[PDB]
Length: 330
Image (cartoon, rainbow, N blue to C red; front, side, top):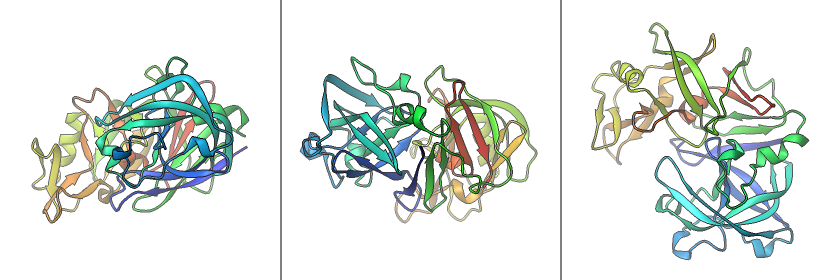
């Protein structure tokens, strides 16, 4: 089997992407944030504290003839950005782009943090990291991909995120029309439960390539590119007037700037992030200070190849017995 679904930016900045997901019988379609940095499929629901729901579409398990309470199971998650959610668990039928999993754990939120409430466009998350990170207790649950894998034509999914435009998540096949040149594959460590890999270096603009190993995670659920402070300083040094602002929470730059590109290495291959991808707009409405899309990972404890990086590539998440990651230009 295969699946193919369009993923759509939630706003003009590509702050996140939402993908429609069918849950239950009859289908209830919710727009979920596909997150290769976590491993829980959780939704706003009829059980979510009413004051914490503000415009989201909810899953109502009592209206699904295929829903079953997973008795005794609870979940609770906290994300790198400080947001969180928790609740109980149902199993139900879940379909993405025509690919169906029966008995998928659907984690129903009883509580969500303010950041989730305040974002009316995201109805929940669909985790695509390794199932070892799933938070369901006392019986850990499998991700949608893990459940689908054996049925797929090939045990893979691909992320093709657009810049200021829709893109595609495919399951079970590689669309050879969706990228240019060849796909370069690179080793993955699953030891921390992430799609963790090592970039071979970087360049700023038309500058020379610096060969240096940068360990990090491919994370579709993180907006920005978080890299070591040395790398980030080298990038912003090429933008007149750019500075790190403790008050704002990262590098800012004059909105009048033209940003240089940023290149990262994948083996001997190179992925170029155009300068425009690195612009996250005014820090507040009407400001001439703009927020940068490349930020320091210092104090996160891990480098993160978030959407800023991934949307410059066609990315293969290869879930074979020994997982790997593939990157192509597009």
